[PDB]
Length: 23
Image (cartoon, rainbow, N blue to C red; front, top):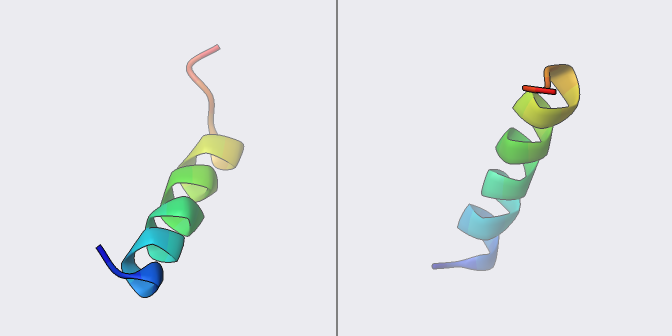
């Protein structure tokens, strides 16, 4: 995995996460 790929995952993960949560 490359820093670009990783950071990208963090953006998407936190993206959908912050947007909505299972609660």
